Image (cartoon, grey):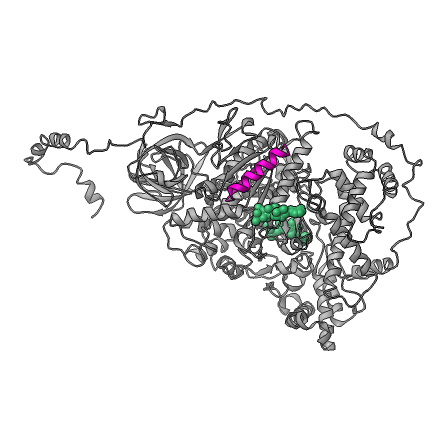
Amino acid sequence: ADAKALDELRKPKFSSKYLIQHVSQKLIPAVKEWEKSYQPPVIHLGRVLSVGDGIARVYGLKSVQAGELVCFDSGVKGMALNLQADHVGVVVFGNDSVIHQGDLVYRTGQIVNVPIGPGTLGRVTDGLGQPIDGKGPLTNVRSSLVEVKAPGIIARQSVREPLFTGVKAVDALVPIGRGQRELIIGDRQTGKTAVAIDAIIHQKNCNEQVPKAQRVYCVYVAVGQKRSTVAQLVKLFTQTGAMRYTIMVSATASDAAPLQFLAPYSGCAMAEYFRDTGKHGLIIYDDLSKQSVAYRQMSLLLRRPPGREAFPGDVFYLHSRLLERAAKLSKELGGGSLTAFPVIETQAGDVSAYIATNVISITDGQIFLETELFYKGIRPALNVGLSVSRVGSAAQFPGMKQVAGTLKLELAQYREVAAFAQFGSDLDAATQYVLERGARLTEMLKQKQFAPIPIERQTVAVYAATKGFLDKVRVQDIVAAEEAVISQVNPAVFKILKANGKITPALDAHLKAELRKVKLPGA
Amino acid sequence: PAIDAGYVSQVIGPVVDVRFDGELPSILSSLEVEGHSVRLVLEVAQHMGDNTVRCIAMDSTDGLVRGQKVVDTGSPIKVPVGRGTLGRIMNVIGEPVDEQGPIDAADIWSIHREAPEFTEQSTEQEILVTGIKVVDLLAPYQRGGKIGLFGGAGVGKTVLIMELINNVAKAHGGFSVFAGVGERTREGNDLYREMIESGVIKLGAERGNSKCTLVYGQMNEPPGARARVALTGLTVAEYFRDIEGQDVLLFVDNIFRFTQANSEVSALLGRIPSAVGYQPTLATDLGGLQERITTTTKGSITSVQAVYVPADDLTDPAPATTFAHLDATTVLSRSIAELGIYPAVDPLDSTSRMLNPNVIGAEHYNVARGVQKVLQDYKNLQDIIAILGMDELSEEDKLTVARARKIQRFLSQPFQVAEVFTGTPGKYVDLADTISGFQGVLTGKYDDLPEMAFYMVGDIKEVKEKADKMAKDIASRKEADNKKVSEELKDIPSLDKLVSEIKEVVIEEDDGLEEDFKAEALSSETVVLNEEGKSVPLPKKN
Ligand SMILES: Nc1ncnc2c1ncn2[C@@H]1O[C@H](COP(=O)(O)OP(=O)(O)OP(=O)(O)O)[C@@H](O)[C@H]1O
Ligand SMILES: Nc1ncnc2c1ncn2[C@@H]1O[C@H](COP(=O)(O)OP(=O)(O)O)[C@@H](O)[C@H]1O
Ligand SMILES: [Mg+2]
Ligand SMILES: [Mg+2]
């Protein structure tokens, strides 16, 4: 059954034609008898051969590009995933029940793209950019590709600008640079969403007082969540006015797994408008560990061979090519930035899992949220020993960098004199000092939800904690004492700390002065 | 025009089948795709059988149409080598990604070759002093050796490989090659900008006096570019080893990403997968790559490779296969790093071929084996220490636990590249100093000093000065009441005087987003292409 012995069968070798002109005059009446039974032949459009599991195999589509957004005649959109010799494998961005064998597939002529621009700000879109908030179509916008490559080495610079998150534990201990990527990893129900929400509300609070080029435009990608949670979140953002600066990409739990897979890429494409135009973006991929599960479903329904835990093996590349787009661009590219906050949910605190350790190898640091600290009321439940942000270090608030160093050392000593005391039977009265200073600082660090704190009022409070001015309150009233410190100290010193950036000698003079004339409620 | 120009038969992610009407290219030859938005280079992997080759793409395949002209180049991926590549950054296929103009190539070498033969193997063992206590004591590196840093996602092998760059790459007089295979682009930019301000990379007309060439295939690249950029780094280092004949340092950050990228493209090559999820050809792919990073009779490559381990699992087949190819494995632990001990080197899992008394001397060998015996006896005791406490130990066992906690803290060391995020300045420790210090802790000369005086200090002098510093404070805790600098007239303008020097900012409240924006008018219907390619609204049936 050779090939050169089959190309020799292209030339005619019959020399006897008693059947060519027998059927050549009888073929056209036969074709005209069975004419309404023919579907019209399809070459540059497509026709669905077989649809199932959210993957349509499409005959035709002779000139589709790889990774191109195709359209079914139902209206539901697809993506030309693998072009094959006879068919095209299409992943269906939506429910595959509206697709039937024989349906016309129309090629849109463009690789998978979403609308990006200023007019997507304020809006709740789905995973493909189509708006779901009901207030119309996206005006003042332009379409751009979701799978653009991240900027290279020469298109980057080091992070310098400090991107305050409004959380005292984070902005004191784990400071976040402006083009950084910081992982929010923790168990279920441990305040992972709340840190990102406090960052978004704080960016609303900071945008009203920065000169229009230091403004940070957030994007929230809600992958795999419930739709009621996204509805309550959009309600919260409109109640606080934050929606003027944020976009809400949402591919929820009922949505198809191509939509949950693609929603971080569409969200990052929307935020890369702000990165590529000299402005600053912040993006939160809420539960990237659900995007990995949707991609694992897509890979196992394409019968791709599974690897660790069941994952395809390019599940590292899935998250790496997404998070690498969160850069701090150079001066000749505009100076824009994009900060990423991927969220990963662990199971029973196991951070040595597959997707967890994949994203720890991508991001610049981690924010660990322990369930034991969360159940004891310490909220945000930051594992202070394990959480790291070294790229945001030497890129933070100088006034906070002055105070946070001794805060970090005192918390390190507190953790080790708590590990020293597995037991209450032997008191030392020299470690008891740091064991009470550490329980002072832990109570100082915890704050309540949806009220992010400006960076000067964090600096002044941690200044009042690591120094004296708080040793009279036991452990209980340190929240009330910190509120009395913020309310009773003259509000000019916050302005001096904000505009000078650091604590000058003329400033910590008035810090030691104004802190002694406040009245602490635990006496 | 027709023959030696095939056409794209099918595209499956990073895997492209090309159909040649005649004269198929050889396996490993590079093919250029015409009509793409960027330069797409396909390296031929297989001959599928019906005049079809199967290729791996060095860039993304988005936009590839199943008729596109693919031009054979008749040769593999060939990259510019020479001294003219020093101080440059190259990608996998050799294009300069530093915006410094073209690369002055002495030669253009194919990235695919064979390992040097058994006749060309150099077998000579000489120590490479790094200035790291745990490395120079328990797993000492070889001067032409292959060195693997095994790590578990956050345990510190990039900090360790950057400290090895800082400590070794300047004392070493030859050239240096950094190959970044599947790592952060932020780390590549940091390495470039700190090799410029160290003078290791000199920009402009002083480029020939650079000591390091960078090749980068970082983790935003497709799986075809990460599976071949280690070979571009090896080609740049192999030209210096063979033709230039001199000693090279090859730092490969994450040689695991080579294996992982081959297992990404390997499922689409139509292979039955092996263990955990890997390619069947893992060991021979890694062997064919790693057998070329050797020293020969003509030159020398000291090879430091970071090796990621997938889920803190050293029995995963990519670390477990990499372990055979290394003269010195430095295994970094997660539980060591959670004790704060940095570098997080597991002292009972990091081996070397140089821990041999006929190589490093009997005193060094004996102090290394004594340290390892003390730490192993502590590890044997920890299960009954955790339950029963230390009160149930024998007294020689309490001596074992005390000396083992002391040498556990003493293997910790501050780094000169961790001084930017810890505040502690980093200490280079000479080999005789760490030998004498660990010998002194083993004999018992420092049983009076506490545990935390050994933590993050350079020498055995600095544990004594840290006990002097810790002891003196043990009284110094308070009595800083007044006579301060925090007065109200001696340095001090008033608070309302201090507000009056605050400068005003201009607030516009316009958000500045519609300045240079061309807004596409989206349609009310899905615009699609019909059979003729015209942009038609979506027809109304289903
Ligand atoms: N700083 C805080 N202070 C007090 N309560 C908090 C704080 N942060 C979060 N919580 C509470 O913890 C609960 C869980 O918060 P959140 O939804 O942020 O966690 P999560 O990690 O998103 O959990 P899940 O991922 O399962 O939704 C919320 O009901 C919230 O009220
Ligand atoms: N020698 C060290 N000293 C102090 N901290 C370290 C050291 N090595 C690693 N770390 C901490 O571990 C983190 C991860 O380091 P890195 O080398 O990037 O890890 P990996 O490359 O294994 O993911 C760093 O951000 C740092 O906080
Ligand atoms: Mg959540
Ligand atoms: Mg690394």
Does B222 sit left or right of B370 as displayed?
Answer: left
- Using residue B177 as the reference point, say whether residue A97 is left or right of it: left
| Rendered image quadrant of residue B432 | bottom right
Q: Does the magenta stretch include residue A288?
A: no
Report which quarter residue B207 is drawn in.
Answer: top right
Q: Above or below — where is B466 with respect to A232? A: below
Residue B305 in view (yes/no): yes
Query: Residue sitting at 21 percent across and 33 percent down?
Result: A38
Which residue occupies the foreground of this view, A62 or A294?
A294
Vertical arrangement, residue B383 with respect to residue A221, above or below: below
Up the image or down, B381 lies above or below B268; here it is: below
Q: State which region is magenta.
A: A220-241
Taking depth in this image into account, of A156 and A428 the one nearest to the observer is A428
Relative depth, front residue between A499 and B440: A499
Q: Where is residue A463 in the image (x, y as percent from the top left)?
A: 80, 44
Percent x, y of residue A27: 12, 32
**Residue A429 image offset from top left, x and y in percent:** 84, 62
Rendered location of residue B344, percent (x, y): 65, 58
Q: Is residue B540 left or right of residue A297?
A: left
Q: Is residue B112 visible?
A: no
- All told, the count of numbered labels is 0
Side of B532 relative to A443 (left or right): left
Q: Is residue A235 magenta?
A: yes
